[PDB]
Length: 29
Length: 32
Length: 30
Picture (cartoon, chains in turn cyan, red, green):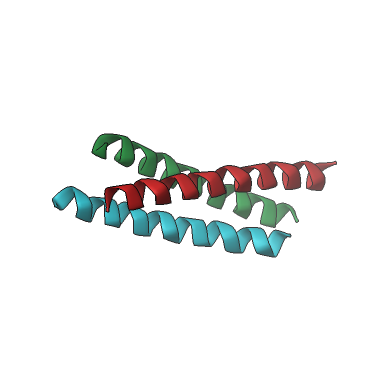
């Protein structure tokens, strides 16, 4: 469970950074 | 595009909430 | 819509960073 948790948290962070830049690119439009 | 990103942020927020519940549970377990 | 979306994304990133810190603390405890 600890291994899965660390993996899911790191994936969530990378998805959050991706969405933040996608939102910034939309704000440009 | 706007609805796509609104949908994504609600999906990620839900995953974030459930991970916080899991963290809470494991913190309890390792401290008892 | 944009400002509510931005607000949610910031919320999300603050939660992901909080979870990252909590996972590191638990990993040291374990």
